[PDB]
Picture 1 (cartoon, rainbow, N blue to C red):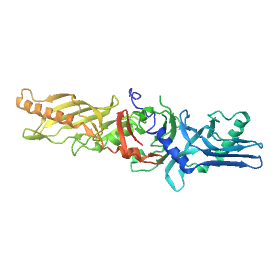
Picture 2 (cartoon, rainbow, N blue to C red):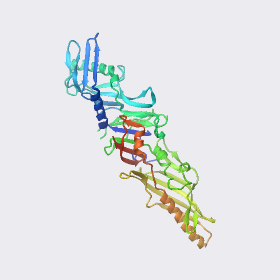
Picture 3 (cartoon, one colour):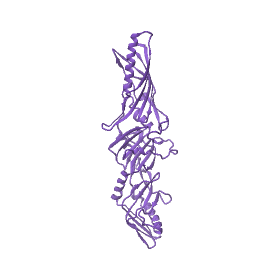
Picture 4 (cartoon, helix red, strand yellow):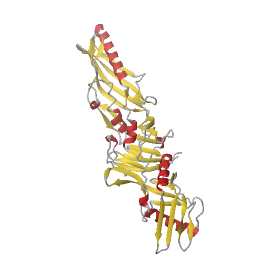
Length: 419
């Protein structure tokens, strides 16, 4: 449990999803251009008006927490106050606008991450800089700031850009999010993250800490699954794939060591398949089995068992095996698997009548074959459904991806792809 922080970290969350702002900006720009967004606001009693036709909206770094920082360059427009009109062509404001997850009234099972403009009684829109180009000053700046907010709030219905769609239900049930937060992150580009938990546990004490390495190797899209979810949903149903028909998922379980970590144990005797040694078949039994993450990217497997001589069951061996099995993702054939240990360790104890050399020779062979059989069977393949995983819950701009680029095990399990 000491090595919990030494690899990739979900920081107490279950599944973390990320997208590059470079990717989002592409779609946001298309959205602003295609819809020819203009904001008007008028107040005849107070003799004020404003018109803004936007060049673009562009996300930039520096956004705090659950705000995006954005530039909203105005290509043309004006405001008018005390019989004075001010030209807004070439004015380049920097705002911060809150994102929130919104309900869809005809579908409880999809949430959408969108801009939240709030109201005059909150700060869901903040003015960072009135004009990055330095053209507004004094009274002009003061009135512009007021009228900009007026115009944004009044024209809130015009902006429905979907940053991400979130599926409450899905084909991959173990991913279904119960609670979720948005966080913007600035790497040493910029990253938009959604942090999720898949149960109703208390999140009020979790921070908005996120591991920027989720979008490492210049990845466009990524996700990080907790150690515990990886063990439960990717390892538990595959570790016994080479152990024969009598050893299956139901013989094992995950022991939790925190909300986000755990290890795997057997819950019953593991009845190995029959092994033919000379003329007879022999049936090893594994009584204790443990499996935990080791050095972030390996499984350390410790087990104890015995094997009795068929037809002479009084004669038997105890054995113990310790195997270290490294995760590999082959980027060519798309297989994700745990390698067989090339240098496993073992020990054994024979139980034989003193001086019985015949039984010794038989037991020696049976014990060796049993240990080698088990050692060779401890490596196994994951099901590669990684494109489906990255498309299951969060679709950034409601778009699916097609290409996974990297798959890493480092405490958490990280799938990265192209947008």
